[PDB]
Length: 218
Length: 218
Image 1 (cartoon, chains in turn yellow, red):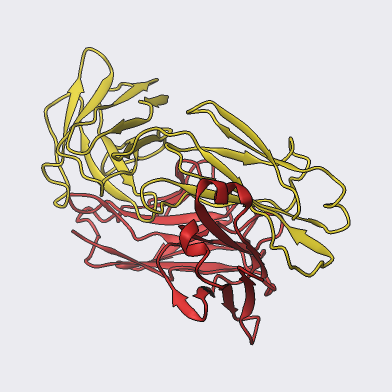
Image 2 (cartoon, helix red, strand yellow; image 1 turned 120 degrees about the horizontal axis):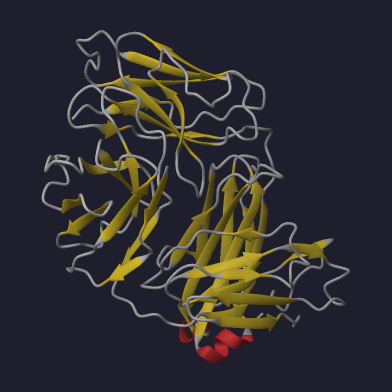
């Protein structure tokens, strides 16, 4: 058994989104297929299930009229017509097989990302985080390298080819006005920073942005 | 719709301890046939959920014996004997009695260890962002426990809340600590009119808030 889904989808608010569900390794049109909505914040909410054989559909009382499923008997694929989409439904969608009153939910999908916004794909903006001019030299010192104004996700902010990998921290993406802003930090001994050359590198595959930047003291 | 109530919301337990989580139904979910149909789901960060317990009186084919499930006609309890490094994740309930089907609230489950001292580090903007025309002040708080911590921004002694980006990650594996990033974005013209910028932290393991302040004109 194996399940396939469509790739990432972006669109302006108000239009429709079509996502496909492919199933193999079993009788595709013999039992229910249900989809799950996972908001990137919390909770799991379902959207509905369909039986690819007959036109038997049901919906949750909260998401009535928001999506309309569709099945195909010739090709083993399930579709979903999406109604007027708002910025409150941008979440991840899973598909799964289900058979009521008996053994059920033994497999899943892989995950499909739906990012609905109004911004435009912009290259990142890299900036160093240098400490202040007046600072007390302790036994160790922390670092910083920031990336602002990029879309869409993801981005890979690393140090010099993995040389400084212990004590790194990458935070989730959070918006400020309309775009993202992510920082990277690591702690290094204070007797090494004035000597060893360190450079933070940023890789954005969606825009093909490979930018390195050296951090120098004041 | 029959809502689930999972207790508690978060149950930090150490390695080797027995942890029990209750999942109560708002109505009776016992079917007239004589069998109650409930599913337990385990979701890991960045992966699709797995199966551990279907038909609570039974066990899934492929899960080790460390998991168990029990309960009366309405109250249900999932029990774990020895929490391992693999058992990290999020739990979910699923009722299969009435139409339609719905999920639970989601139970957060991680490991627990002793307290840690937070590491606070402030970073003023660099010369590159000044050439651009902005001011990004970053405040990292790494290696602290528990999540009970508050971050406050002061400008010349006044509380500031606009432009605050607060982000946090999950519990790391090698050190089992927490991290929190606080970013403050302002214009360069405002950076030349104020004097003192301060990141303050209040945590349980500190009787006094950790203060990190810096002045513009020094």
